[PDB]
Each structure stands twice: as C-alpha cells, then as structure tokens.
Amino acid sequence: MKTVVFAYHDMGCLGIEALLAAGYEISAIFTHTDFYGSVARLAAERGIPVYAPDNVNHPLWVERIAQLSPDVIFSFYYRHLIYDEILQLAPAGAFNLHGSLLPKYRGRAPLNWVLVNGETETGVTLHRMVKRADAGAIVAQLRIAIAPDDIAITLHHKLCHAARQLLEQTLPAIKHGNILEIAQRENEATCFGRRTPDDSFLEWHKPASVLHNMVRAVADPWPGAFSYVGNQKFTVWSSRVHPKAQPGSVISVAPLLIACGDGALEIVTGQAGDGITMQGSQLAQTLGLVQ
Amino acid sequence: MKTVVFAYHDMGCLGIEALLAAGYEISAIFTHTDFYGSVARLAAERGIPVYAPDNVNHPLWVERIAQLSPDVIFSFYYRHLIYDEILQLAPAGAFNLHGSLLPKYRGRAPLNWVLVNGETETGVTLHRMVKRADAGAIVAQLRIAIAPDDIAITLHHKLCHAARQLLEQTLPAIKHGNILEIAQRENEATCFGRRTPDDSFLEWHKPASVLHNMVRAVADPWPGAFSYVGNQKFTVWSSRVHPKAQPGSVISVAPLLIACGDGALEIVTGQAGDGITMQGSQLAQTLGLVQ
Amino acid sequence: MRVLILGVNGFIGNHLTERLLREDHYEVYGLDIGSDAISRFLNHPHFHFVEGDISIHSEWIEYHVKKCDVVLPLVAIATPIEYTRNPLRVFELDFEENLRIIRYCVKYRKRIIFPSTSEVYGMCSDKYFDEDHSNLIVGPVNKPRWIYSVSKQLLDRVIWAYGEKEGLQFTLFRPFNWMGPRLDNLNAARIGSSRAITQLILNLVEGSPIKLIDGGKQKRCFTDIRDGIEALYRIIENAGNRCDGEIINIGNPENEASIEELGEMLLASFEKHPLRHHFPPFAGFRVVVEHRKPSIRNAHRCLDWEPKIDMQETIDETLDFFLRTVDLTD
Amino acid sequence: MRVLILGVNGFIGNHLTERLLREDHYEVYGLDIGSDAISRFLNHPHFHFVEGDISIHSEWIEYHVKKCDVVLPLVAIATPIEYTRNPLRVFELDFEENLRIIRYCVKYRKRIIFPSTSEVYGMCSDKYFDEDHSNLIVGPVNKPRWIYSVSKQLLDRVIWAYGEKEGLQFTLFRPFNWMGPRLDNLNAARIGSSRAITQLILNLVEGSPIKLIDGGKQKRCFTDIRDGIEALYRIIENAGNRCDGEIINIGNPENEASIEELGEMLLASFEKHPLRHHFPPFAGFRVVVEHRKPSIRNAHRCLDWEPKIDMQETIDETLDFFLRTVDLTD
Amino acid sequence: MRVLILGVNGFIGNHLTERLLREDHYEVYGLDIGSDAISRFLNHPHFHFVEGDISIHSEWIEYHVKKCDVVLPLVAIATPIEYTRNPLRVFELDFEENLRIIRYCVKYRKRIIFPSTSEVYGMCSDKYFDEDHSNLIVGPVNKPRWIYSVSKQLLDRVIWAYGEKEGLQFTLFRPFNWMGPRLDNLNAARIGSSRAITQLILNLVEGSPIKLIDGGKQKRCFTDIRDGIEALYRIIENAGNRCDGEIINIGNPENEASIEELGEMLLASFEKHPLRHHFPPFAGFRVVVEHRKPSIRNAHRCLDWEPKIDMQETIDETLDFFLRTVDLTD
C-alpha cells in the first residue's frame, strides 16, 4: 500500500516508523519547518522525499500529490488544514491520529487542555478524515489514565506510547481493507482552539486545584502558567495544592503559598520574568513578597 | 564541605548532581541564560540559589561570593572567565571539569575540535584552576575512545558518562583534602578558540576524510558543516567517505558524491539553505546538481 | 503679561494659575492635552486653554511663544524607573522637545522660566546644594539612572549659553519636593510634585507597603506648595530684574527627613485622619544620593523669600486633601 | 481604542460610528470638512469631530494618526465618469493623498484598515473573485477608465510592502455594492455606497430613465450595510489578530443581479411604496466587466462572518429610507 | 544638443555615445559612478563625464537636467531573481528614483527619452506586442515576479500623464533583447543588454550548464545593437517631431528563437570559434511568458526604421567580442 504522509513532532515520527514497520510504501512526507523528534530528519535519513510548504491547499500541491498516486493518506500531528481536494485523492481514504478520546477534545492541543480541565483520562484515536475536521469515524481508540502528578511532558510520552501500540495493530488492519468504523456522536463532541498566552494566565480567585492543573498543563517544556506581582510577570513551573484571606494574597513565603478562591497554591518552583528558575521561597524574595 | 558552583549544560547538571551525591553543600550556582539539561531548572528544583549574571568579574559578585564563604569552588562547563579575585576566595581551591585530555585541547569546544581533527580518543579532566585558563594541575583524567561513527552528539553523551564516573570518585577524594595533582606540560598543550561559522565551511580541495570529520564534528544538533553550490548554501548533515576530477565537482547524484582533494565525499543527508533535511539524492536535485 | 504654561494640567499649573489669576494683570495661556486638573479655570476670562502636545506640535507652540511674554515649560518625565526602562523617551521629551521651546524663546526674545531639577547636583558632597558653587557628581555611563540628571543639566548649560551669547532672558528654578493639594499622578509627564510623598500617600491609600530602600536613611527636604508657588510667582514678577540669568533652588531646608521619618509622619497623620477607615490597614515598612538639602541664599537675595510652613502642617494638609478627593467607588 | 475615520461624513462613517458607539470601549475621531451626515453624534461623549481635508492638511492629519490607534481612510473619488473626465484629480486624491496617510501609520506604528476596491479584479475571468488567487485584468493604457482600478491596486501593493518590510499592521477590505440608509451623494468623494443603486433610486426619484448599458446584462452583487458594517466592525475588533495582513472581500455573493433585474426589483418596490405618488411616472428602461461576484472565504475564516439579509429586504429598506428622507420642497 | 545619459557606464551608454560623437552637434553628458566601460571617450572634447548616483544625488542631477536638452535615464535593476529577492530595492531604484528624474524634466521643460520594458506586456496573448493596442497581462499580487513589470508600466502612465497635463515632451522606448559588443555585467543596474544572451555566453565561458526552464520552449526576439542604437539615435534626432508622445518597441521580430534554439546557435558559434579552447567543455543543456515578439509599426512610422542584421551575424559578433575581451588570467 502506498501512502503520502503529513506528519510532525514525536507523533509524526512514530507514525512514520509504524507505517514503515507495517510495510507501507511512503512516497512523500509533508511536514513543517520549526524537544521532540524531527520528522524531516527522519524522512531525510530514510530517503523519503519531504516537503514543508506553509499551506498545501492549492492546486500546485494537489497535483504533486496526485502524481504520487497514494492509495491512502495519513495525518500524524500535521498542524494545518489538508483540504478535501487532496484527501479525496486516496481511494482507501485518509486517516488522522488525534491525541484525545474523540469526540471529546477535537481541535488543538488536546494534551494541554485535558490537563487544564483536570481530566483523569485521555487517549489516542485513529479516525477517518471527513469534510469536518476531527469528526470522522473511529478506526480505533486507546485510553490512557492521567495521573495526578502527570504534567504535559509525562502525559505526552504516555500518549506517544499509546499511539505506538495503537498503530502497530491498526495499520496492518487498514492495509487489509476498510474497517467498520465507530461514528462520533456530535452531541458529545467538544472542540478547543489554539491556546493563547492568556490561556495560561493564573487567576487567583479560582480554586487552587484548577490553578494547579493549569500549572501541570503547560509545565516545562511548555511556556508555563503565569501571573503578576503588580506589574512583574512571573511563571509558576511547579506547584502543590494546599487545603481565609484575599485571593492572590501571600499566605507564606517559605514555602511560597498563595491564597486562592478555595484552598492555597504553593509555588514550588518558578521564575520572575525571563529570569532563571528557582525554588518558590527564593522566587518570593526575588518578587519582593512578604506574608 | 561548602561550595559555590559555576555550571551550565549537561556537564553542569551532572556535576551538580555529583556534588550533591558526594555530600557537598552547594550554597549557590552561577549559570547562563540560554537539547541539554538546564542547570537553572535543576537548581530551582533542588532549592539552590541560582544566578546568571553575564559577567562575574566585578566586585559586586566577588563580595556576594565571599559572603557565601565557599570552602571550594567548582566550574562545570561554565563559559566565561571567573577571575582570580573570585577563585581565591576558596581555601581548598577551585576545580574545573574540562572535556579533553588536557593539556591537549584547552579552550573552547573540545568536543567538536577533537572530531574535526579526527582524534581517536578524548576524555574528561578535572583540574585545579590557576591564573592561566585550563592549565592547572590535574586531579584526575579519564580517557574515552572516539569511534569512527561517533558524531558530536554521541561523543557528548560518552563524555558526560565519563565525567559522571570521574566525579563520583574524585569529588569524595577532594572532600578528604588536597590530592597530589599532575602538572600539565606546557610544551604539550594545544588551545582552541570559539568556533566561527567559517570553521564548519567545507573546502573540497581537502581530503574526503577530513571533510567527513568536519561533518561529524558539527552534525545535528550542532549547526552542520556547509558549502555552496555557486551562491546557494547547503548543509551536509551526514556523510560517507569513498576511495580523478576537479575537487568540488559532482561525481554522481544518486548517491550524491562530491570529488575531494583525495577520495570522494558522499552527502548522505543534507539541506539546501534553511530548507528541510533530505537524502543526498534529493538534495542533489534540489540544488540543480548533475553528474 | 501673557504667561504661557506648557503642561498646565497638573499641580504647578493649578497652583500657579490660581495665584496669577488673583492678580489683575495676568493672562494665562495653559497648554495641555487635557483639562480635568484645571477645569474650574476654563470659564475664567483671563485663562486661555490651549490644546497641545510638545512632541507633536511645532508651529502651534511656536505661535504661542510669540504671542506670549513669558514661558514655563513643565512637561518632562521624572519617574525614576522610566530613566532605566524608557531612557530614550525620557531623553527625547525632557531634552529634545524642551530644547525646541527654548529656541522659540531665543528666537522671539521671550523670557523663559525653566524647571531645572534638584537631581542635577547628584552625589554632591556639600551639605547644602548651592546653585552657583556646588560641583555636580554623577556615576559612570554604566549607571543609566543618571541620564535624567545629566539631560537636565545639559539643558541648563544650553540655556545659560543662549543667555550669554544670544541675550536670552531666563531664570532657572529647582524645586525640592513641593507638596500640597492636587498632586500630579505618579506617571504624569509634568514637573513639580514630590514623587516620594505621592508614592507614600498612595501606599497608605492602597494598603501597599512603604519601601525603605536600604532602611530609608536617605534624607530629603520637603516644601509646601504655598511656599514654592509664592517663590515662583516672585520669579514671574521679577522685581528689579533681579532674577535675570539666575539659578534658584526653591525648597525648605528645615523640612528635612529621611524616607523612614517621612513614612512615620505620614502614618501618624493618616491614623489620626477621620477618613482613615475608608482605607486598608497599614501593610508596613519594607526594607529593600544620601542627602539633598538646598542652599536658598539665591531665593533670599533675588526674591526676598523664605519658607513659612512647618513640616507638620504641609504633611497634614497634603494628606487631608488627597484623602478627601479620592473616589471611593474607584 | 481610538478609531480615526477620515471622511466620516457619509454612509460608512454614519453606520460605522453608530456601531462603535454601541460598544463601551471606542472613541471615534471623525474627520471631515462637514458634519451634516452625522450631526446626531456631535454631542456624543465618545465621538470627536475633527475639521479636515486630506488634500489640504499635512500636520493635523499626522497628529490625529499619532493620537489614535486605528485608521480608516474613506476619502476617494470612485465616480466612473470622473476616471475619464478628471483622471488626474482621481489619481491625486485617491492615490497620492491616501499614500501620505498610509506613511503616517507606518511611521507611528498604527493599524490601518484600508478600503481597497472590487474594481481591482477588473476583467478577471474567475466566477468568484478571490483576494488571494485571482489574477487582475485590465485593458491597455488607451482605455483610461482603468486608472482608478490600477491606482487602488498599486496602493494595495504599497500597503503590502510596508507590511512585509516595515511591520505595518493592516487589513485591506473590498466592499461589493453596500447599500442601506444614508447613502452617499453620487459625487461625494467618500467610499462605500453602491453607486449603481444610488443612481437607479435617483432615476425613480427624479423621473429620469434607467440606462441599461448594452441591455444591462452585466451582473453585480449587492450587500446590506448591516452585513457589511458587521464585517467591518469585526475587522476592527480583530479577534485573535486573525485579520493581520489579510485582504477581505465583503459582499453577499447570493445577492446577484444584472442591472436589468436590479432595475425591475427597485421598480417593483417603488410602485408598491406608499410615498410613490410624490415622484414622477417611470421614464422607462433605456438601452445604451460582465460579472463581479466575491469569494468570501477570507471573511468566513477571519471574521466568522456570513451575510444574513436577502436581496429583497435590503432593496426595500434602502429604497424606503431614501424616499422618506427626500426633501419634497427641494 | 546636450544629451544627458544617466547610467552611461554600460552597453547603451557606450554604443549611444559612439553614435552621437560621430555627429558634430552633440555634447554628451554621461553620468555614472564609474567610467571603465567608456574610458576611451573621457578625453573626447564633446563627451563630459559626470560623477553621480541617482539614489544619492538630488541637486546635482537636477542641475544637469536643467543644463541639458534631452535626458536618457538608463539606471534600473532588471535582474529577475532580484524581483523576488530584493523587490523593495528594485521598486525604489527603478520606480522612485526615476520618477524624480522625470519630474526634473517636467519642471525644466526638457525632453525625456525613457526605456520602458518589453516586460510591460506580460502574458499578453497577441502574437505581436503592440504599444498602442495590446492589453497588459500580469499575475495576481501573490506572484511577486511582476513587481518589475508593473513598476515600469506605472512609470509609463505617469510619464503619459505629465505629457497630457503638463506638456512634457517624451518618447518611450522598449528594447527587445539588444545584443552586441560591450554587454552589461549581469548584475549591473543599467538597462539595455539581453540578460538571456549574457547568461548563456557566460555559461559557455565558465563551463556551467544552460538551464532550459521547462525545456526552454519560450520564444524571444533578439536585436543587434547596431539596429537598436540606430533606432534610438533616430528617436534622439526626432525628425518632424514624429516621436513626440510615442511609445516605440525596438526589436527585430524576425530574430525569433526559443531559449533552446538560442542555446544551440550560441553553442555552434562557440565550438567554431578560434578561442574556444580557452574555455571549458560544454556542461550541457539542463531541463529545469511563452512569446515576446514586438510589433515595430511605430518604429516604421516614426523613425522610418527597420532592422538590417540577421540572427546569425548578431550572434557571431556578440560572442566573438565577448570571448576576445575576456581576461583569461581572471
């Protein structure tokens, strides 16, 4: 079975490796220019043509892809719209690997949003690509638990591991033909957009648990959850939730505890502005905080 | 034993971890703002004060360090001069971890220069810091072999492993007191400066083996060895040496072989300008090359 | 006598305009981009509001210089953090744009009354900073806080040179922590109100802490605006032309206090105030140029002036008015 | 958010100003040489009338660009006969004077929202004119009607270049026959109202004939101002900065009609109108670019917008308001 | 007759200067930043070298326009890769700086002889590109190669407008691949020499391959400089004032070849050349606007001109001179 692949990031790399292990002939890989593996380097190393146009929804690319005559198309964490004029070129269809328990968390950054929302589980889904983005029928879905101490990076590795497990068996299954797919129920779908810097802004009137989840959701290597001490921005890299004061006020400086709408949030590590990461107690002194 | 540490990069992280495992009390860590581990994050996580001034050779820092009263000072891949007014504050002395078989390869980027020069061995050296940079007496030196297929990143991991092994036994030894150090013989020393973009420029009149070593020396994640096809820059990410034409001329395009002063260099993978990495054969077409 | 005040919508503009309108022979042209601080003079027959901005306008300001007799340029940023956060803008506004106004006065042979700054003396070691004799001491170029001090000083020297060479009639004045009712906002680019007392009163009003940088042992002098404005009014009157080419410190050297003591005085006056309960509890003192006392011999000589209001009455009056005019819903 | 509308005294100015004043965070600066079309906003606290003319003023417009955050230049002659009768004046005003305003935005790093024109596509053969993909087709230099189209296009390219090279923040918009209440006069040099419907309504109002140039088989799209202004308002809001560097057709591609059909629709709505008897009998249809339909994918994507008003309601509402406000004694 | 050539240090400057100095009533002012291409005229009594650069000088060029009678601005970048790699600089030099020179001619009522470009026709589908009748066809704005074509066209229109409105005396000319001895360097910002033949001759000289973009089936016309310069000389003479306000293609429409055929012709002439052995072996043809043939009726009418040199003699002469003057040590 020959295929044209759209891929990026660790998921893109493992998807390409899985296709290769399943005997697929990858005619070309479409990716993006830039801690994760490089799909371009993997393609370059495997001798697979690789392209990184900013936008493929143009006849120039439709024709180039048509000439490659893919039987099937795969999208593994490609970040841009691949329009139907391209996807319809593959008689066996197009399939996308999405990092959530679809229909929940369609859209962008499901890895981060499930942590923001304090979900206790998430998963990977391989689904048919239809007109409507992330809504096509499910070939297979594999759930993973989210542990209280998982942060974006540890959950990312778990998702990649699940993706490897899922693809290892589903790719050969697709090679044998159409699989009876599971329809997504629109009434159960949720969709998220790309996260803006504002989406990681800590608002102290919220419950400490919610803020703690935000810290976990964008912990290093992600940008970090942030707030301000007056006009000084600071980032909270790691935190701890604790069980009678104005929200946002300092309860203690060592450890650094901030009163929230409910409970308190201990800033275990963080940084002031673009300064270096330090323990919360030191950050408190750096920011001029006092009980 | 209390200490003030200057550290950066993976070597900095492992040096800090080794000091901690050896029972040293780290009062403060001096590092730099920016694939390797972050010394700042490690310090922030371990609750150790951390500073990243651009330059410490000023009385403000001498006084701050003096107040910390270190018994000993360590430098683990810190990149700037730490002048004597600071180093003399430690009665037990100051020690630096350098990535080469001192006195050879004093100076900058010994990891890359040993590959550029095709050395078959290198190592890590812990030495006393004296007035003259990288010239102090040796506490211990551990050699590692450089394999023909090592590139900068694989050699880097081997050096870090050697550093861990060396520090694990020498740090406790230093804690017990002065060790009879091995003098460096100046007549055997070599020194290298910081590498400029020009230092990774491939000149085809040279032997293919020398160019191959250059490719290995700055392979990804380093910047890559480069050349030009007329006015078009391209980078050679990986290569192979092969055993009657103008140097720089194309012998074949699949595989892509370039005639050198002696032998030929196959460009296994590379990229054109800031384009994506691809196999040499594709790069040849991208660059408009023909036999 | 047509008096042109550039940057009238503030502390000095308010108090100066009040004073000049008491007298029957002043027409005040108050130039600014807003009028909220002086809105009660807008209907006065001898006040004339002029729309303007000294960074945007060329010809309009030039016109008003020609039309008028005496000019008081009060537009400048003197917010310390700004000296380091936005040094170029401090330089452009405080130096370059004011230099244009100076040159308009030179060209149309008008008198200029220019606010120099007490910051010009810098780390001068004299106990009394003397306009005619004290050396000016600043740090190296790698200490950028001094850009404001040195910009203002060079402007003084340029005024001095126009005076010597081109017959410019000038008086320079240096206010030392003037204070009273209708203080400028902390980030208004208008000269005149003590940033140290505004900040402290703000701490009490907001319930934030009072920062004592290194214990707050640095000593400053504080001057009631009734004293200050009286002096400035006499410079305007210029009896006997005795202010021509003069540099005049205007402050009360007996109103000396460290920031710590100023802190305690304000707090005492605050805790005693009938409206104190509208404001939060005291967040406390927070430990985080050592003296700046003016010589006032020039003001004695030229203006026959000496300050009449004690520390405590100025503190009390300044605080009282501030608290009473705070909008408690915002 | 300070919004500077140059040429506010018209259709777009009126409807845009109404929309922005509904929202609590807009200050509208409406620049023009008259105010009769917007006189009911003159007393609004967040509307600011500015006297001006973009051919006469340099510094005054420049000032107002600096003072404001976003700029909408609506002054241009788009009267077809003028392209041939007064081409130099069309070029000078529409190109040269607007280019100055563009350069003011570049200089003070302000956002510009610029009315490009649907005429830029010219004789493009795509069925749907696409801002990002359609080729632009004009006639030879000996066909001077194209001077307007090409002046506007070159201005777009210059904006584009400032965006690429100088970090100008822009959005370009292309209106397709916007229509509703308060249409510009036919010879007002202000962009926005459909000249084709104004002319036709005028024919009915005056009792002159409707000219069908070659049978009036050329097809156009027509857009209710409620739809159009909603889109423009969203460009101003710029949610997610999704309009940055974008070119956006704003029209309703389903409201397609030949001039003949538009003629009959207007006439039907006219003959049915309760005030029709104040106007002369129908003088008749008079036989004397073949399609111009917008792609609106960019508006879909950037603004999440699609048009909501059918042809018939826009026709009826546009005609009704016009007739009701005609002065029957003049 | 004082003839001002801006950008004289090149192909057209050389050949034009030779021609005008044959005649007894010309004074040639050759403006440039160097003189190596024309150094043999520096001592001629009726040649006057003028130091200059049209991007740096204002007054000096203006002066020389006033001093002279007719002006030929030959400074422009027409290197295709530059249209996409340095579009702003192409626009600034080719459009903006030449527009200043045009306005100097308007102001001092001087005649201008301006090099328009054959690129103005773009993808025109006429078989013969006609200055007075052919439509000009370019791609969308997202195809930036067209910035050169459209800049030059707008400049033509601006010249045309000055002619109509301000009595500017002009002739526009469009060269089609002029070639002969003393070709411009490929990256010289001077109009006139066929970049296609210079490149190909360079390939043979360097031993690089000849690129046939999509097989090199696109057809071009090639014109001997003896024919071209004769035409330009007649435009200068302007017998009967018959060139006033005219646009004149100057090319030989019978010298048509695809790039492939031009390739083979050059190669044949090369392999036959007595100095061929100083150059490398042929690196080969490398597969990587489809027609551009001029109408020359305007040149027939205005100049009584028709081209006299066949393809083969121009090819041979052009190649021969190039090879003979190559510095073999460098």
Image (cartoon, coloured by chain):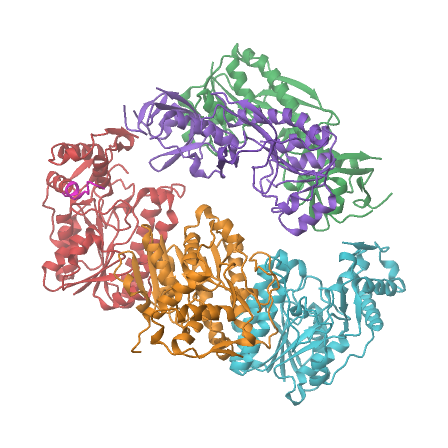
Chain colours: A purple, B green, C red, D orange, E cyan
- Depth order, front residue of C283/C253: C283
Q: For residue B258, what is the image quadrant?
A: top right
Which residue lies at the image location 51% right of the left edge and 81% below the top edge?
A: E165
The quarter in which the N terminus of chain A is drawn is top right
What are the residue bounds of the magenta stretch? C321-330
Number of numbered discs: 0
User: Does D216 sit left or right of E28 as displayed?
Assistant: left
Q: Is residue B136 above or below residue B180?
A: below
**Which of the 4 image quarters holds residue E79?**
bottom right
Left or right: residue A7 compared with residue A1 = left
Q: Tell which of A141 and E327 is nearer to you.
A: A141
- Spot occupied by residue A201 in the image (x, y as percentages of width and height): 41, 35
Residue nearer the viewer, A183 or E204: A183
Q: Is residue C284 above or below residue D250?
A: above
Q: x and y percent of residue B217 in the render?
A: 69, 32
Q: Is E229 left, or right, of B84 in this rendering?
A: right
Q: Position of residue C214 (x, y in %)?
A: 29, 30
What residue lies at 21% left-to-right and 30% top-to-bottom? C282
Is residue C43 among what the camera can see? Answer: yes
Q: Quadrant of residue C111?
A: bottom left
Observer-nearest of A281 and A77: A77
Asked if residue C328 lies in the magenta stretch, the reply is yes
- Quadrant containing the C terminus of chain A is top left
Say whether residue A246 is left or right of residue C181: right
Q: Residue furthest front?
A: D272
Whether residue E61 is visible: no
* Residue extending furthest toward the top: B176
User: Which residue, as the protein is rendered here, is positioned at the far bottom?
Assistant: E240
- For residue C75: magenta? no
Please state the horizontal and vertical placement of residue E311, each as a whole percent of the image.
82, 72
